[PDB]
Length: 124
Ligand SMILES: CO[C@@H]1O[C@@H](C(=O)O)[C@@H](O[C@H]2O[C@H](COS(=O)(=O)O)[C@@H](O)[C@H](OS(=O)(=O)O)[C@H]2NS(=O)(=O)O)[C@H](O)[C@H]1OS(=O)(=O)O
Picture 1 (tube, protein in one colour):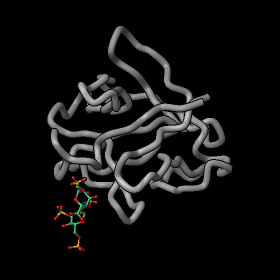
Picture 2 (cartoon, rainbow, N blue to C red):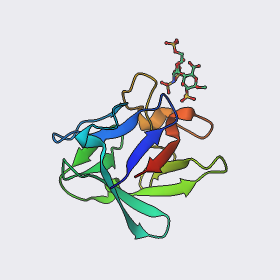
Picture 3 (tube, rainbow, N blue to C red):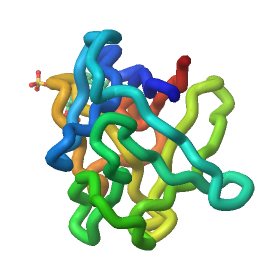
Picture 4 (tube, protein in one colour):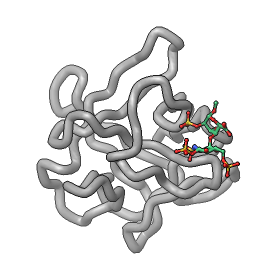
């Protein structure tokens, strides 16, 4: 599994068993272990290992994690020039997976390039 360390505050992306998404700084949290699975080159799904749920971005920018894999569950994974990764919705293509400084997720419609919120380092 991987954990996704967000540059914005040092929060790891967390997927709760019930589908809620947020961030936490605890490396020991069971709900931050993720499986990043390649769908094709540069395209991934993000599954919470504990939750058996896949990260999804909704049409209004909400993040949540669903039991089923749908078209809202795929993301462009890009290694940026600063060597952080970004995860951009394959369906809503201007919007990024992001965490705010409070550890709450950032609405997709409020994200974009240049923001710290969208930058993640995957780690083992
Ligand atoms: C360089 O890091 C970016 O800016 C940080 C900062 O200026 O504090 C921080 O931004 C968040 O906090 C600011 C200030 O908050 S407050 O007014 O003191 O309460 C917010 O203005 C900002 O929200 S907003 O959408 O820009 O209005 C917050 N951004 S966050 O994504 O919600 O965290 C962040 O560390 C970072 O912002 S980022 O570049 O948009 O990620």
